Image (cartoon, coloured by chain):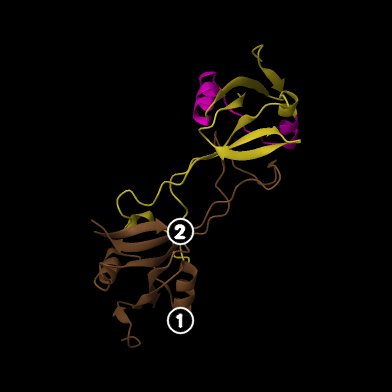
Chain colours: A brown, B yellow
């Protein structure tokens, strides 16, 4: 028992978002409805979601890499300390963001993508 | 220290004038029973510099080996690698980067592609 267009599974209500938007905008869209981009915790959950998708479509999941700092490691395993470093002006290079989508291939699975391309999306709410 | 090497505190340093990739520079340091240089203090940086030529650029023992990205769920649910459903051969291998030390007209680190030939510094 969820709001009209939503579908229920166990503790959660699920929304399949028909519009195509960036990851951030898709997240904001779930947010106003009291939700988040979908978090998939179990195989049964994934299987439930698959039942609700169209094979001709591709959807942002609430799974991403916010980029920023690279995980610099010393070659022997000496821990890394941002204060004992001598990076030149405007250095190092930052790591680009990355977002995950789910779609149907040649079956159903996830894929990493640039965050700002528009995709459909899935909102989840307990 | 073996005569080609220079000494500082409890360590021996080797400046290697061949230009190779990071992996081979490390291989080269390793077969001498050493490693690409790991810099732990400001004073260890200062000493290494003394042994470098202003016209040269050198790999350090610092890198990002790439591999898998740091995927997070949006609500901060733990990313357990066991309940993922990535397509075969996805997600993309995150790329390797590697640090170098060189002189800008002072001394500092740049991050570059690991397969580019540079000189190197070994510490043992």
Q: What residue appears at the point 64 percent right and 39 percent down from the top-left corner?
A: B110
> In the depicted view, which residue is nearer to us: B107 or A116?
A116
Q: What residue appears at the point 32 percent right and 85 percent down from the top-left corner?
A: A5
- Would you identify the image quadrant in which residue A13 lies? bottom left
Crowding at label 2, few (<14), some or many (≥20) Cα neighbours within 10 Å?
A: some
Q: Is residue B90 above or below residue A46?
A: above
Residue A80 showing in the rendered view: yes
Dot 1 corresponds to which residue?
A: A34
As helix, strand or loop, the secondary structure at mark 2 comes to loop
Relative to residue A104, is residue B104 drawn left or right? right
- Would you identify the image quadrant in which residue A57 lies? bottom left
Tell me, yes or no, whether the highlighted magenta stretch contains residue B39.
yes
- Would you identify the image quadrant in which residue B43 lies? top right
> In the depicted view, which residue is nearer to us: A26 or A76?
A26
Disc 2: host chain: A
Disc 1: host chain: A
Magenta extent: B22-46
Q: Is residue A113 above or below residue B92?
A: below
Q: Is residue B124 above or below residue A53?
A: above
Dot 2 corresponds to which residue?
A: A114
Rendered location of residue B47, percent (x, y): 74, 28
As helix, strand or loop, the secondary structure at mark 1 comes to loop
Crowding at label 1, few (<14), some or many (≥20) Cα neighbours within 10 Å?
A: few
């Amino acid at each position: 028992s969820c709001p009209t267009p939503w579908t229920s599974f166990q503790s959660s209500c699920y929304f399949i978002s028909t519009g195509m938007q960036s990851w951030t905008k898709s997240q904001k869209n779930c947010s106003v409805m009291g939700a988040d981009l979908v978090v998939i915790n179990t195989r049964e959950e994934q299987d439930f979601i698959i039942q609700n998708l169209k094979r001709n479509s591709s959807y942002f999941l609430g799974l991403s890499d916010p980029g920023g700092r690279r995980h610099w490691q010393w070659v022997d395993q000496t821990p890394y300390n941002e204060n004992v470093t001598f990076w030149h002006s405007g250095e190092p290079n930052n790591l680009d963001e990355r977002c995950a989508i789910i779609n149907f291939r040649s079956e159903w699975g996830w894929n990493d993508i640039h965050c700002h391309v528009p995709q459909k999306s899935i909102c989840k709410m307990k």
